[PDB]
Image: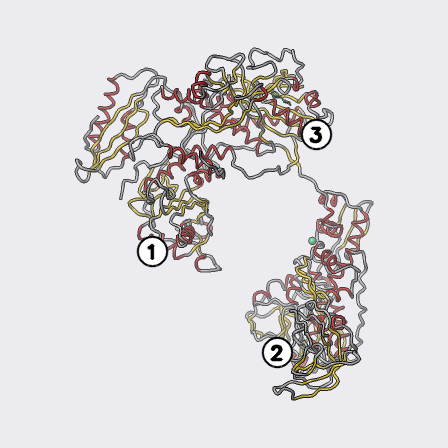
C-alpha cells in the first residue's frame, strides 16, 4: 500500500491560445448553423483586396501607409476579403461562409472574422437580428447594442455596431452592411436576382472584452504563464 | 401470406410479366419477399399411359412396364413403385429430360432392358407425397401434354408480407383489388350462387357480447365429410401454404384465402340446444381441435352453448365440436368478430392461425353473408347435404362505423409538397372502394369502404393518393428554416474527450449494457442489480452497475487470444439501483470507464515491457481531468473490487465523481487478469463547462526556495502541501513536491519529503527579510502540527 | 428579423480535423503560440544562411521585416522571452503559415503553405518526485511526432 495523494507520473495538459478559443467560439455559432469556415492566403494582390471591393483605385479608402506591401500590387491582408471574393467568383449563391484568419496593418498582426451571406433575398432587418443574437450569445449577456451608420465601399447601407461595455461606454465591436451591387456584379452575381450582407469583427476586440484583458500585446508575447491562465 | 399468381390472374390478369407484377405489389405497400415457380425448372416431361406390367425381374422387387406417351413405338423402363391398380396414366420424363439436379436420365439399359426416360417422380418432381412410388396419382389423363401445363407447375407463388394496417389484403380478393386499382382495371370476381333452403332447422341468437356484431350460422344435414377434395382446391391451398385435412376444413380454408372471411364448421350432434357467442367464464376450460387444452379468461370471447363451450371465437375450434369421421350434420359459422375483441388473445396460448391474424386485424364486416353463400355452394357441389335457412344474429348499430372524411386539394398539396391532379385524386380513391362526393367546388367528401380499417383521418386519404400515383413520383424539395445562433457555453466536448483518451493510448470499446449477475456480485458482493425480466442468457441478465461487468469479458476475450496488452475506454451508461425501493429510483449515469492491462507503452527496444504502477495510471487520469479544467482532491476509496491500498476516490467540492486504482488482486486471480487498472468518471463532471478569468502577471523575478521535511509516512502530502499554502500567505503563489526518500538514513515509519516554494511579488522585488519571515513561519507550523525536522 | 435558408447536408469526407489536432498536441504537453508572420532577417539567416527571405517594403521595425521562411524565426524569440523570465521548461506549437520564397524569380512564385511547428526546451515532464528533471532525447521527441502522424493515419518514412 502506497500514499495515494502523491502526484501522478505523466504529462501536464497543454494550452490552446485564447485568440483561437474565441475564434472557435465565434465560428461555432455559424458553423453548426449553416455557414462553412473558409480560409485563404495572407499575401494578396491588389484586385482581390481593393478593385473587386468597389474601390476604384486612388480612392481615399486606400491608405497606403498603414498597409504592409512588397511591390505595388502585392501586400499583406488588411481584411480576409480575398476568400469572400474568390468564393463569389467561382461559386454561385446561396453563399454562407465565415472567414477567420490573421491580417496585418502598420501600427501589427491581429485576427478578425468576416462573414458573408448571399441568397436570393436578404435585408437590413435580417442583418441586425443575426448580429444581435451573435453578440448576445457570445458574451452570454443581455447586451445593449447600438447601430450607427458608417461607410464602406462594398456595402450600402453600411453600419457599425457597439455594445455598452465597461462603465456605460460604447465600444465598437464589428462593422457590417448590405453587400454593394457592384461587388456582386463584379464577381458574376446578378445584384437584381440575389441579395447579400456581410460583417467583420476583430477577434482581439472580442477576446479582451470576453476575458477581461487590457493589453493585447500579451496575445503575441506568448508568456507561458499567460497562456496557462486559459487552461 | 403466400398466394398463387394464377389464382390471382383469375381475378385480375394485367397481361404483364411476373416481375413487373411483383414490382407493382412492392411499390403499393405489399413487399414481396419471394416469387418462385411452384416447381424447380426442368425441360422435357410429357404425360403417358402405362399399358402392361410384368413382375419378378432381376430378383428383389422390380417390374418392367411399357408406357404410351403418344410415341409411335414406345419403349420400356423399370421401376419399383408399389401401387394398387396397374395401367395408370402418369407424366413421364423423356430421354433428353433435365430433371432438377442434373438428373438427365441417359437411357442406357437396366440390365438388358433398354430404357427411354423415367416414368416416375413422386419426390423428384418436387411434389410432397406420403408413400413412395406415388408418382403422379391416376386421377385423370391430359393425353400427353407437358406436365408443366397440366398441374400448372410453372405457376409462381408470391410470398407477400403485408403490414397490419392493410388487413384487407390478407386474401386473393384484397390483393386483386390492389392489382386492379394500380392498373386501372376492374376485378371480375367469380359469380357467387346462393344455396336455397330445403329444410327448416334450428337457430340461435346471442348478444351477450359486443365483439360479434354480425353472426351467420347455417345447419346443413347429411354432408359427406369423407368427400374427395378436388385437385384445383387442394393445389390452391397447397401453394398458398395451407395443408389439406377433410373436405369441410379445406373449403373453409379456401374461402378464407379467397375472400378473407374465416369460417368454421361444427358437429351439430355435439351442440346441445342454443349456441352462444359469449365471454368465457373466469378460468373456463376447453380442449381445442389440437391436443392442447387451454384455460381461458373472462375477457376472451368464445362460442359456447347451454352447458359446455365449443370454440374460441375466431381463433381455434374445439375438439368437442370438431367434425370427425362420424359426423353427419354440421353447423356452418360465418361471423364478423370485432378486431379489438380478438387482438392479443390468440398470442396468450401460443396460437397464430389464419383466422386469428385476420380477425385481430381488419376483416370485411360486409363479408359474412358472402362467405356463407361461397361455402354452401362449395359444400353442396363437392359434398352435398340437406341445407337449411341462414340464421342472422346482427346488432347493426355496433358495426365498425365508416363516417365520411373531408379532404381538400390544399391538404393534399401541403402534405405531399407537389400538386396532383384533382382528376387523379378522385379516380384513385373511387376505385380503391371509396364513394367520393364532390362537395362545394374544390373539396371532396370521401367515405372509406367496408373492408379497409386504416382510413380515419384525411392524412390516410393523402397516403392513398401517393400510393396509387406512385412513390417514384414524389418531387424532391428541401425544408427551410431561420438561421438562429443557438446558446452555447465553452465546455469540454465529448469528441475532445475521446481525442484525449485516444491520445493517452486507449481504444474505445462498446460493451453490452447488461452483464452477468455473478460477475456483478464478484466486483461488489453487496450489489442489488436491476435484473431483466426476460434475458436471452444468464450472462446478459443484469443491468451493469459498473462498466467493468461488461468490459472485463471484453478484456478476457482479447487476453485469451494472445494479447498481452489491451486498453479500453467506454462511454458509458451505468445503472445505479442500490438503496432503491422502486424502479423509478433507478439512476442512469453516463460515465467514462478506463481498463488497462499489460505494459503502459507497447513493446519496444527502449525498455523491457512492465505493467503500470499506480502513478502511471493516476498520471493519465489527472490529464483527462485537467483536460476539462476539473479541480480534484484524492482520498482513499473503499470500493470492494479495488485494491484498498492503491485505489483513490475522486472528489470535487467534497463529493465523489468517480474512482481510480487497480483491481483487487484476489479478483485478478479469479478472473485471470494479471494486473489491471480500472477507473470510472461521471461524464457530467468531466464534460463540464468552464470560464477563464485573466489575472495580471508580475514583471519582476520570482524566488525559489527548498524545504526538506523528515515526517512520518502516515500523513498525506496533500495535507502538508495545503498547510504550506495557507501559512505561506499571499506572497507564496505556488508549491510542488519534487523528491521523496525512504532509504538509508531514515528510520522505519518516516520519510524525507522535499518541497519547492516559489515566492512571487505583484508589484516590487522581494527582500530577503520577508522571504525568511515566511520560511520560518512555514517550518514552525510544520514542526508544531506534524513534529518534523526542516532544512534548506 | 432572421435570415432563412434551405437546410442541405453539405459534402464532408472523414479527416483529421484542426480542432482534433490541437487536442492531440495539447495532450502531448504543448501550449499553442501565435507568433508574428514576419521575423528578423538576422535570425532568418542564422537558421538557414542560404535563405532568400521575402522582405517588407515598409517594415515596422528591423526585427519584423522578413516574412518567416520557417515558424522557428518567430517562435524562437517567444521561447527566449520566457527563458529571460525564469522559465526552465517551455513547449510551444503553432498552426500558422510559412512563406517559401527560395529559388523564386518573382513575387507570384511565393508558396504560402500552412504548417504545424513544435518547439521544446526543458524536461519532457514537469518537475515531480518521480525523476530528476532531464531534457528530451531524439526518441522522446520522435515518440511525440509519431503519435501526431499516427493520429491522422499518416504513414511516414524517416531519412
Ligand atoms: C464584403 C466583403 C469585404 C470584406 N470585409 C467584411 C466587412 C463587411 C462590412 C463591414 C465591415 C467588414 C467581401 C465581398 C462581399 C462583401
Ligand atoms: Mg394508411
What residue is shown with label 1? Answer: B670
Question: Is residue B210 at least partly visible in the picture?
Answer: no
Callout 3 secondary element: loop
Q: Badge 3 local density, few (<14 within 10 Å), some, or many (20+)? A: some
Measuring from the top left, give residue B586's x and y in whole percent.
45, 49
For this view, does B403 lie left or right of residue B770? right
Q: Mark 3 lies on which chain?
A: A
Measuring from the top left, give residue B229's x and y in whole percent.
72, 77
Callout 1 secondary element: helix
* Whether marks 2 and 1 lie on the same chain: yes
Mark number displayed over residue A120: 3
Q: Nearer the viewer, mark 2 or mark 3?
A: 3
For this view, does B341 lie left or right of residue B696? right
Q: Nearer the viewer, mark 3 or mark 1?
A: 1
Q: Badge 1 local density, few (<14 within 10 Å), some, or many (20+)? A: few
Q: Which chain carries label 1?
A: B
Residue contact at pointers 2 and 3, CB within 8 angstroms: no
Q: Quadrant of residue B193?
A: bottom right
What residue is shown with label 2? Answer: B320
Measuring from the top left, give residue C109's x and y in whole percent.
58, 22
- Looking at the picture, does residue B472 appear above or below residue C103? below
Q: Mark 2 lies on which chain?
A: B
Q: Nearer the viewer, residue B440 or C26?
A: C26
**Which sits earlier in the primary sequence, circle 2 or circle 1?**
2
Q: In which quarter of the image is the C terminus of chain B?
A: top left
Q: In which quarter of the image is the N terminus of chain B?
A: bottom right
Inter-mark Cα distance, 2 to 1:
60 Å
Amino acid at each position: 500500500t502506497i500514499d495515494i495523494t502523491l502526484p501522478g507520473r505523466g504529462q501536464r495538459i497543454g494550452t490552446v491560445h485564447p485568440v483561437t478559443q474565441v475564434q472557435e467560439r465565434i465560428c461555432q455559432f455559424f458553423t453548426k448553423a449553416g455557414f462553412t469556415v473558409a480560409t485563404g492566403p495572407e499575401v494578396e494582390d491588389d484586385y482581390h483586396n481593393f478593385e473587386a471591393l468597389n474601390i476604384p483605385g486612388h480612392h481615399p479608402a486606400r491608405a497606403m501607409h498603414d498597409t504592409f506591401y512588397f511591390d505595388a500590387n502585392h501586400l499583406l491582408r488588411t481584411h480576409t476579403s480575398g476568400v469572400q471574393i474568390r468564393t463569389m467568383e467561382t461559386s454561385q449563391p446561396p453563399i454562407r461562409i465565415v472567414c477567420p484568419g490573421r491580417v496585418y496593418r502598420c501600427d501589427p498582426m491581429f485576427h478578425q472574422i468576416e462573414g458573408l451571406y448571399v441568397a436570393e433575398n436578404t435585408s437590413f432587418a435580417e442583418l441586425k437580428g443575426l448580429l444581435i443574437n451573435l453578440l448576445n450569445e457570445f458574451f452570454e449577456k443581455d447586451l445593449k447594442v447600438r447601430f450607427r451608420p458608417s461607410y464602406f465601399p462594398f456595402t450600402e447601407p453600411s453600419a457599425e455596431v457597439d455594445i455598452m461595455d465597461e462603465r456605460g461606454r460604447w465600444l465598437e465591436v464589428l462593422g457590417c452592411g448590405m453587400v454593394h451591387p457592384n461587388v456582386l456584379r463584379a464577381a458574376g452575381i446578378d445584384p437584381d436576382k440575389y441579395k447579400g450582407f456581410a460583417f467583420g469583427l476583430g477577434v482581439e476586440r472580442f477576446a479582451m472584452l470576453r476575458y477581461g484583458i487590457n493589453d493585447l500585446r500579451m496575445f503575441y508575447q506568448n508568456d507561458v504563464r499567460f497562456l496557462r491562465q486559459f487552461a | 401470406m403466400k398466394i398463387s399468381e394464377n389464382w390471382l390472374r383469375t381475378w385480375v390478369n394485367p397481361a404483364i410479366d411476373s416481375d413487373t407484377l411483383s414490382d407493382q405489389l412492392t411499390m403499393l405497400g405489399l413487399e414481396v419477399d419471394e416469387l418462385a415457380s411452384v416447381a424447380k425448372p426442368f425441360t422435357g416431361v410429357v404425360v403417358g399411359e402405362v399399358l402392361t406390367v410384368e413382375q419378378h425381374p432381376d430378383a428383389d422387387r422390380l417390374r418392367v412396364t411399357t408406357v404410351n406417351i403418344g410415341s409411335g413405338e414406345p419403349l420400356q423402363i423399370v421401376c419399383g413403385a408399389p401401387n394398387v391398380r396397374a395401367g395408370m396414366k402418369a407424366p413421364v420424363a423423356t430421354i433428353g429430360a433435365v430433371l432438377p439436379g442434373d438428373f438427365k436420365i441417359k437411357k442406357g439399359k437396366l440390365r438388358g432392358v433398354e430404357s427411354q426416360g423415367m416414368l416416375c417422380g413422386a419426390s423428384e418432381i418436387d411434389l410432397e407425397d406420403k408413400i413412395d412410388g406415388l408418382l403422379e396419382l391416376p386421377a385423370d389423363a391430359p393425353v400427353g401434354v407437358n406436365i408443366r401445363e397440366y398441374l400448372k407447375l410453372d405457376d409462381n407463388v408470391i410470398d407477400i408480407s403485408i403490414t397490419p394496417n392493410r388487413g384487407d389484403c390478407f386474401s386473393i380478393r384484397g390483393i386483386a383489388r390492389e392489382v386492379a386499382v394500380i392498373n386501372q382495371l376492374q376485378m371480375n370476381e367469380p359469380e357467387i350462387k346462393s344455396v336455397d333452403a330445403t329444410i327448416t332447422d334450428e337457430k340461435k341468437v346471442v348478444i351477450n357480447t359486443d365483439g360479434a356484431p354480425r353472426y351467420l350460422g347455417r345447419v346443413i344435414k347429411n354432408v359427406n365429410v369423407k368427400a374427395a377434395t378436388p385437385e384445383w382446391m387442394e393445389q390452391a391451398l397447397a401453394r398458398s401454404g395451407i395443408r389439406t385435412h377433410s373436405i369441410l376444413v379445406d373449403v373453409t380454408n379456401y374461402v378464407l384465402m379467397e375472400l378473407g372471411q374465416p369460417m368454421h364448421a361444427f358437429d351439430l350432434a355435439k351442440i346441445e340446444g342454443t349456441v352462444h357467442v359469449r365471454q368465457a367464464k373466469p378460468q373456463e376450460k376447453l380442449q381445442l381441435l389440437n391436443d392442447q387444452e387451454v384455460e381461458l379468461q373472462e375477457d376472451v370471447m368464445v362460442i359456447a352453448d347451454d352447458q359446455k363451450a365449443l370454440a374460441i371465437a375466431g381463433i381455434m375450434g374445439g375438439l368437442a365440436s370438431s367434425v370427425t369421421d362420424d359426423t353427419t350434420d354440421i353447423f356452418l359459422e360465418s361471423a364478423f368478430f370485432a378486431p379489438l375483441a380478438i387482438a392479443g388473445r390468440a398470442r396468450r396460448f401460443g396460437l397464430h392461425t389464419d383466422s386469428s391474424q385476420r380477425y385481430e386485424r381488419g376483416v370485411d364486416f360486409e363479408l359474412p353473408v358472402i362467405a356463407m353463400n361461397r361455402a354452401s355452394q362449395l359444400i353442396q357441389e363437392l359434398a352435398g347435404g340437406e341445407f337449411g335457412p341462414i340464421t342472422v344474429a346482427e346488432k347493426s348499430d355496433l358495426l365498425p362505423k365508416r363516417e365520411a372524411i373531408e379532404l381538400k386539394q390544399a391538404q393534399v398539396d401541403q402534405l405531399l409538397g407537389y400538386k396532383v391532379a384533382a382528376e387523379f385524386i378522385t379516380d384513385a380513391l373511387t376505385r380503391l372502394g371509396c364513394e367520393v362526393t364532390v362537395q362545394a367546388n374544390g373539396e371532396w367528401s370521401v367515405v372509406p369502404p367496408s373492408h379497409r380499417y386504416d382510413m380515419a383521418i384525411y392524412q390516410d386519404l393523402i397516403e392513398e393518393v401517393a400510393r396509387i400515383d406512385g412513390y417514384d413520383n414524389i418531387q424532391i424539395s428541401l425544408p427551410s428554416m431561420d438561421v438562429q445562433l443557438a446558446k452555447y457555453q465553452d465546455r469540454f466536448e465529448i469528441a475532445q474527450l475521446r481525442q484525449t483518451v485516444a491520445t493517452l493510448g486507449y481504444q474505445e470499446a462498446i460493451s453490452f449494457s447488461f452483464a452477468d449477475a455473478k460477475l456483478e456480485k464478484q466486483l461488489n458482493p453487496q450489489v442489488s442489480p436491476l435484473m431483466l425480466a426476460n434475458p436471452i442468457s444468464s450472462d446478459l441478465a443484469a443491468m451493469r452497475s459498473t462498466l467493468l461487468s461488461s468490459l472485463i469479458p471484453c478484456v478476457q476475450y482479447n487476453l485469451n487470444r494472445q494479447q498481452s496488452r489491451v486498453r479500453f475506454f467506454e462511454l458509458g451508461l451505468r445503472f445505479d439501483y442500490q438503496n432503491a425501493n422502486s424502479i423509478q429510483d433507478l439512476k442512469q449515469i453516463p460515465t467514462l470507464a478506463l481498463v488497462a492491462v499489460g505494459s503502459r507503452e507497447p513493446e519496444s527496444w527502449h525498455a523491457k515491457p512492465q505493467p503500470m504502477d499506480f502513478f502511471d495510471f493516476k498520471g493519465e487520469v489527472e490529464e483527462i481531468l485537467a483536460a476539462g479544467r476539473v479541480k480534484v482532491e484524492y482520498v482513499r476509496s473503499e470500493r470492494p473490487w479495488l485494491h484498498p491500498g492503491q485505489s483513490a476516490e475522486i472528489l470535487v467540492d467534497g463529493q465523489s465523481i468517480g474512482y481510480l486504482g487497480r483491481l483487487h488482486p484476489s479478483l485478478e486471480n479469479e478472473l485471470d487478469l494479471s494486473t489491471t487498472w480500472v477507473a470510472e468518471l461521471d461524464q457530467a463532471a468531466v464534460l463540464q463547462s468552464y470560464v477563464s478569468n485573466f489575472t495580471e502577471l508580475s514583471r519582476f523575478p520570482s524566488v525559489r526556495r527548498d524545504i526538506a521535511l523528515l515526517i512520518s509516512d502516515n500523513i498525506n502530502v496533500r495535507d502538508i502541501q495545503q498547510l504550506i499554502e495557507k501559512t505561506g500567505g499571499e506572497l507564496l503563489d505556488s508549491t510542488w513536491l519534487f523528491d521523496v526518500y525512504t532509504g538509508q538514513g531514515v528510520e522505519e515509519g518516516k520519510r524525507s519529503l522535499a518541497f519547492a516554494l516559489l515566492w512571487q511579488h505583484p508589484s516590487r522585488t522581494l527582500e530577503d527579510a520577508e522571504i525568511k519571515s515566511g520560511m520560518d513561519n512555514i517550518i514552525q507550523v510544520l514542526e508544531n502540527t506534524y513534529q518534523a525536522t526542516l532544512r534548506a
